[PDB]
Length: 358
Ligand SMILES: OC[C@H]1O[C@@H](O[C@H]2[C@H](O)[C@@H](O)[C@@H](O)O[C@@H]2CO)[C@H](O)[C@@H](O)[C@@H]1O
Ligand SMILES: OC[C@H]1O[C@@H](O)[C@H](O)[C@@H](O)[C@@H]1O
Image 1 (cartoon, rainbow, N blue to C red):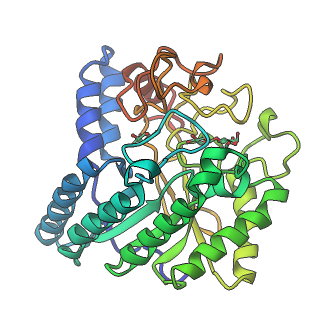
Image 2: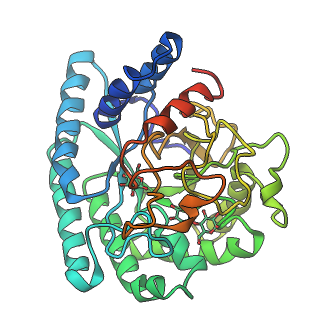
Image 3: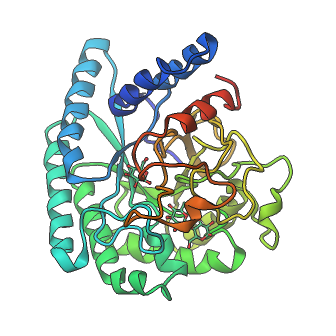
């Protein structure tokens, strides 16, 4: 559409990922692979506000971006993920978070958003693009029979609404997480998904800052598959482009000219999954298509790297309170550390298997 949030901005590179990547690159023994790995720090990624502890980091990113804009004569754009719902990750165990509904969670989440808003308010010269709460709304479309999700539904809807409503007041451009083609892209799920997203968009006042939806976050699907991955049997929407082409018209009819961003950060190697629902630390993945607004689709504002490759999806240690058996499947890299922490061997495979090559 007319207003792509990326037009006219330089993306501020993640300092958090840059620090992980720089340290990772010096441990890659092959010199050629090491320089390729270090270059990953110059590829724009989203930085996750996965705990309240990350909010001061956001302040430093905004302040550094503001200064860099003035020094270089540009307008800077900071890419973040809002990811701290109470009872987070309701249909899995790997990414449970610090807030719980039974321990003051909804109010704590409000305070988390308020502190984020207070940082962003100080730097109106910096644009912010935020992905809102990966997995949450998709779980409310398809997984209401999961009791943790059912019990979390009102809290998720309230909290997501609070985030959208308040981040809009400081001009944040927002893409609500919308799963991926193997989750909400099933033709039968398209309309339930559209109805929920439209309701959420209406509840937040149809703000122009709510641009649309993010897809494939922390997943591995192709944007445009050469051949349909065998895992997609039964679903004519076998890649992200098919999913988006099928979902976007439903949003437009409901009144929302929604646009999309698509994670490709771990899509470089296809055919690594035994089953479509194998989401955890998939062995042999490589970095995918670099971020770009040259997306080939009327509905897609940008290809993006949302999940930072190298950060684990979940522990394979069955003794941890966050153990999910998806992370021990024959196609999951093991042993794997706790979700969100650095997985050096996984990062080095992502570099070596990058497609296009680094
Ligand atoms: O995409 C990552 C998230 O996957 C979630 O599981 C989905 C899965 O991706 C789909 O392929 C399909 O199997 O339905 C699942 C939902 O039950 C998972 O719950 C999340 O933790 C992942 O972040
Ligand atoms: O790596 C990005 C995100 O991945 C999630 O699976 C983890 O739970 C988060 O801690 C992390 O911020």
